[PDB]
Amino acid sequence: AKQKMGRVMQTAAFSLAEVSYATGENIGYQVQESVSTARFKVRARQENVSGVYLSQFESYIDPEINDFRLTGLGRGGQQVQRAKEIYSRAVETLVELASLQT
Amino acid sequence: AEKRTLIAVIADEDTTTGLLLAGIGQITPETQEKNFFVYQEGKTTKEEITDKFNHFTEERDDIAILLINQHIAENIRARVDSFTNAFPAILEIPSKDHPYDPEKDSVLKRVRKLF
Amino acid sequence: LEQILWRVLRGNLFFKTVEIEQPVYDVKTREYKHKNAFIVFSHGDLIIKRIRKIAESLDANLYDVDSSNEGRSQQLAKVNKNLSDLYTVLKTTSTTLES
Amino acid sequence: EGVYFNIDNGFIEGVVRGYRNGLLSNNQYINLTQCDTLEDLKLQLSSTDYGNFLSSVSSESLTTSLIQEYASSKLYHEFNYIRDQSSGSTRKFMDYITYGYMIDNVALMITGTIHDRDKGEILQRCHPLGWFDTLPTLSVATDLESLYETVLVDTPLAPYFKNCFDTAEELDDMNIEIIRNKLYKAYLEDFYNFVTEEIPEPAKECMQTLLGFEADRRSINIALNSLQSSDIDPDLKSDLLPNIGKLYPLATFHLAQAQDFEGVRAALANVYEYRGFLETGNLEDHFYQLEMELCRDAFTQQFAISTVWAWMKSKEQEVRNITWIAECIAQNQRERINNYISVY
Amino acid sequence: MATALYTANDFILISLPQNAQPVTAPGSKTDSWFNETLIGGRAFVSDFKIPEFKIGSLDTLIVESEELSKVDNQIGASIGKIIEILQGLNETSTNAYRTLPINNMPVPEYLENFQWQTRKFKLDKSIKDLITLISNESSQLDADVRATYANYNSAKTNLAAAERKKTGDLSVRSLHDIVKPEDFVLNSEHLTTVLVAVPKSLKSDFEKSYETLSKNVVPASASVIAEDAEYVLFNVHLFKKNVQEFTTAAREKKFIPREFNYSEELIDQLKKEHDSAASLEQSLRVQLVRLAKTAYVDVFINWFHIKALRVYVESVLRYGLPPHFNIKIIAVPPKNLSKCKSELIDAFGFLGGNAFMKDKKGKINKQDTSLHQYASLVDTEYEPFVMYIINL
């Protein structure tokens, strides 16, 4: 898993860079200002694998709750709306890898 | 068992952008006990990195997973190996602009030996 | 191509080509285009990577050939295999859609 | 008009045309096709009007922020030079052109209420043309809506400041966006009226066409953003959507009343123009392509002050295309290539 | 041709096959042809010969030449940087061992008879071996000089920082040699002499701020110890238990307090940092002068040995029997480049090709013309007239 992750995550990790000048500004400051609440909670579910309880992690994203609402300007809405999905779903494998580590 | 549901990040704000978009916690508005960290690679001190790493590791039993840039992972490698506890799960992210380096994953380093 | 060869092989070439009568079709531009073929020999073994790559990127159809006329017979046989039947496709397809 | 328009301004058009001739044409996009790695883009960007300053200071890894700021630095230089050399009426016209950017900049000013962002950082995040030297407005309490008065008395934007205390002030997350949209609509209408009353008829049309395309595009994009988060009131939408489309002012109201994808789809179908929905995966790319094709009409008129406006827009969108190619190469996306504008 | 012009004479190369004759005069030799061709004062050419020690198989030669060209351009850029930085010091803004005797030898008379003899390494080694050695030594020299110049600039900015504090107001402005400790009571915590500084504007507004509102400011001592024509100082005292309240009052009046501890080590630090910065910068400058001279002279010979071998092999694979052919080095004054190049091509292009008469030649790699690129692999166009950009 580790090696193929090394590339898959980076695949969607650079979709943020295009948005910066697609919307014409350094989106980092905005997005950080646009954040005051999480939406991706993880459950350390216990799986008694062969009589041993192992802390597996539940890759649970919250679509009914958003970050500190500051979304879209008029020049990059679609890119951000697809990024918050693709690069967010690039985290379920992360949750599973953490479970594997534990 | 959700005794730790917060995902700490010590990595560049560039990387932290999409993470916060997906949600990695929040800034705690009673003592500014933020569930993450902001760092500039190769141009900001590591003492604050070590302090926040101690905070998330031993002073925070609620941190689900600490995500650390591989760059930072080797920057504070001593600290990285210092704290090895499963529940505060540690997964070192290959840092943006720093291609996947298995040598930069301490847990993967343990995955080297005894095999 | 002749000048590109003039360059890449640095003053050493054996270039033999003849225009192809009865021009042919295509699909990239979809025309009854006018096409030719090439024949060259040289000592480069690995260099042929660039040769075939540039040719195909511009235009090329791989042709495993033989430096003599003996295998010519084998190639004639193998091509004639399909040749004997190729032409059916159209006339077969016709009557069904017609009726 | 015509020759009478040329009594003392026979050189401004010449220098503007000289600058425009430096824009990358289709034969330059032939290398963009060959551009599939950062090294190739750097080599090309050491040979063009953007040549040897996007790579002299930047490293091989072409990052979006450095590349775009370096590209736009010379654009700021040229625009400031033109404005200095522009006549009084043209000076005021350039001032209004920059007023859009500095409406966005004051929107950044007011928006900062949870981070108290530094003025230097903000002016770094927007066009420096939209920043005179300072703005003692952050001295007052920076609430969601507590500086509109301070900025209005500080900036000269009383006309372009549509009242934000009327409906843009609700102490809501919408504030940091609705104030921006309303001020953008106000500035768009003010600029539309200015180009209607000044900027003679060839230059008039060369303005209104692109101004309307931009206003309608902003309407659609902010409508999508509202639909991509908590929705808003149709009256609020009208406050956000530029009420005067400047190409079609009736279907914008239809979109404002429409609160569903089908309603906006209907409001877009009757426009008798481009259809953003149902055929665009990245609507912004198609909008940019169409906008540049439309501003090419500005250059189609040899006698119009719209040449500088079209030139700056074309250069900015070309830098956008260069950054887009650089990034799709970073993601190894060869399909996102050809999204670059092909009119010039 | 030209690479650096102070009083130089430009240099080029050309192939010299020795089985044919010049186009126009089939009864002349290149020495005679040239000396008859070009006007005097410039009509000079020098000879050169190099052996063939290690020869890769035919198919490798192409990539060998390609990498040779790559490193050639790289090292040309490197030495361009070397000379740019050299004259950047401005100690010598002109030729430095460029017109001065090269390695104590005449500027031309150290390369024409230089046939890669053993100077510091074996005069006979494999192609790749020589390439690697030269590349690595050059890289080491470049890294050393670059780090040294970074240190030099660091020292310069240290000098700038030191000189910055010499100008400004009194919030940190030094009071060490013009400060009276007797006017600065320190034995006990009874009267703490605060150092309050104000611009010259508020003379009256300040002079009646202690003797009308304060408490126990020791009389007869509230004045300036030194004035910089823009700001002044005052040795104000106050309690040991109400310092902050009076400081807050003063800052309401918008004064800039100066809090400081009179310590000798601080003055010693000032003097020593001044001396260290200045002396280190100067000594580094001069040591770097020697280092750059050495590295430049060292890389001199290989800089063109590389192209010597390049052509040495390009000719053979291009033309004629394997072992050897006539070859020479062009040594001529400047300002006649296209002039010479005309008869240059005229002399031997007729044999470089033998079935063409064209008007489109050249060798270059940019990304401005897609066709007519001259990139041997993409849109390349004839050039049988090799020369090179080398100069005194």
Image (spheres, grey):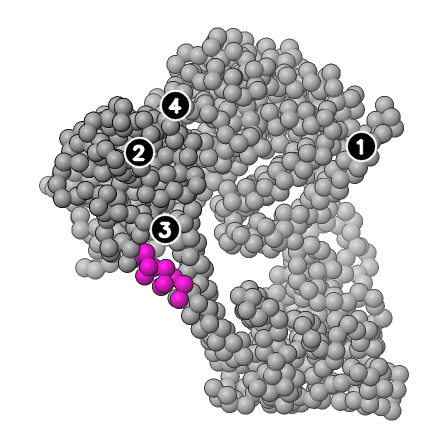
How far apart are labels 3 and 4 at the CA level? 30 Å
Task: Give the chain of mark 1.
Answer: D
Please give the residue where the numbered disc 4 appears in the rendered image: D113
Task: Give the chain of mark 4.
Answer: D
Instruction: Please tell me whether residue D33 is drawn above or below residue B36 in the rendered image.
Output: below
Magenta residues, start to end: E269-279
Please give the residue where the numbered disc 1 appears in the rendered image: D9
Residue in the image at 66% along x and 23% along y: D211
Secondary structure of residue under mark 4: loop
Specify few, some or many for label 2: CA neighbours under 10 Å numbering under 14, 14-19, or 20 or more: many
Please give the residue where the numbered disc 3 appears in the rendered image: B42
Can residue A27 be seen here? no
Q: Are marks 1 and 4 on the same chain?
A: yes
Give the image location of residue E319, x and y in percent. Answer: 71, 82
Can residue E115 be seen here? yes
Task: Give the chain of mark 3.
Answer: B
| Closest to the observer, E179 or E308 | E179
Quadrant placement of the C terminus of chain A: top left
Please give the residue where the numbered disc 2 appears in the rendered image: B24
In-image side of B90 versus D269 (left or right)? left
Instruction: Please tell me whether residue C78 is drawn above or below residue D27 in the rendered image.
Output: below
